[PDB]
Amino acid sequence: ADTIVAVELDTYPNTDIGDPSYPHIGIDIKSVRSKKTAKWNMQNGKVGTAHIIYNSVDKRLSAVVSYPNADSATVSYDVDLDNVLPEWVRVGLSASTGLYKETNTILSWSFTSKLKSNSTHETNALHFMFNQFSKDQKDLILQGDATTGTDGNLELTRVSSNGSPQGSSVGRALFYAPVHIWESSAVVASFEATFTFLIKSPDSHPADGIAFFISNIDSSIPSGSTGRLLGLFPDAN
Ligand SMILES: [Mn+2]
Ligand SMILES: [Mn+2]
Ligand code: NA
């Protein structure tokens, strides 16, 4: 199976599998059952922003999710990614809907990773910024129901011609180039990702969520990972 590290913006409380009884953000280390969560006052229909950071000095994965003029939600977890992920990975965004649904629209996505050599102290870096997603965005690997082009946005999950979200959908978008997330011979390493999203739902409750994730380069959507699995895991273990 794939190896996954992710920050989930979980819009639906699946308490049967460990979710807290409220929308929340969480840090997922090789399991959909978050190692740490924070309550999230998600706002149906408003554009929000997510900020994720990590560095090899503190080895603490943190995320901040908020909406303009509202109190933000923050979650942090100490984890040595060297012991979790392979040296080379791909980064991406994933989202899903299930019995309940929502739009999982990405309006922007940026990422920066840096690795400073212990032998020369010089740095290798990668940075990309997407403010517009075109119909044929070749530097992105779209999987499942993910599409680009409509209004210049990235729709991770299925949406009808009118804009209404569809249920039991799952989709992901990964940056084309592999990323060197960690290296034993690196004195200092870090990464940060930010994305703006618009989650809107006509249902009694929205579901299921969006996530920023890091995985083995050849990662693919696990069969059946719609709904509460967020297109990241094969099961809820
Ligand atoms: Mn959930
Ligand atoms: Mn959750
Ligand atoms: Na945009």
Image: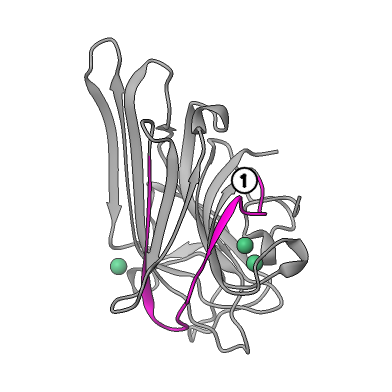
Q: Residue at x 62, y 52 (%)?
A: 232
**Toward which corner of the image does residue 178 lie, by quadrant?**
top left
Residue projecting furthest to the top: 119
On screen, residue 222 versus residue 93, left or right, reads right
What stretch of residues is rendered in magenta? 31-54
Q: Is mark 1 within 8 Å of ligand 1?
A: no
Residue 57 vertical position relative to residue 234 in the rendered view, above or below = above
10 Å crowding of disc 1: few (<14), some (14-19), many (20+):
some
From the top left corner, tell me how far across and down residue 83 is, in percent.
56, 28
Q: Nearer the viewer, residue 155 or 39?
A: 39
Q: Which of 110 and 41 is in front in this view?
A: 41
Secondary structure under tag 1 reads loop
Task: Give the number of marks.
Answer: 1
From the top left corner, tell me how far across and down residue 187 is, in percent.
32, 20
Residue 226 visible in the displayed image: no
Residue 184 vertical position relative to residue 85 in the rendered view, above or below = above
From the top left corner, tell me how far across and down residue 108 is, in percent.
33, 62
On screen, residue 162 versus residue 4, left or right, reads left
Q: Residue at x 47, y 77 (%)?
A: 41
Indicate which quadrant contains ligand 2: bottom right
Residue 84 visible in the displayed image: yes
Residue 43 belongs to the span the image colors magenta: yes
Residue 155 belongs to the span the image colors magenta: no
Question: What's the amino acid at mark 1?
Answer: Ser
From the top left corner, tell me how far across and down residue 8 is, in percent.
53, 59
Q: Which residue is drawn at 28% across and 42% down?
A: 127
**Toward which corner of the image does residue 226 lie, by quadrant?**
bottom right
On screen, residue 93 versus residue 66, left or right, reads right
Residue 148 vertical position relative to residue 88 in the rendered view, above or below = below
Task: Kindly identify which residue carries mark 1.
Answer: 220
- The colour scheme is one colour
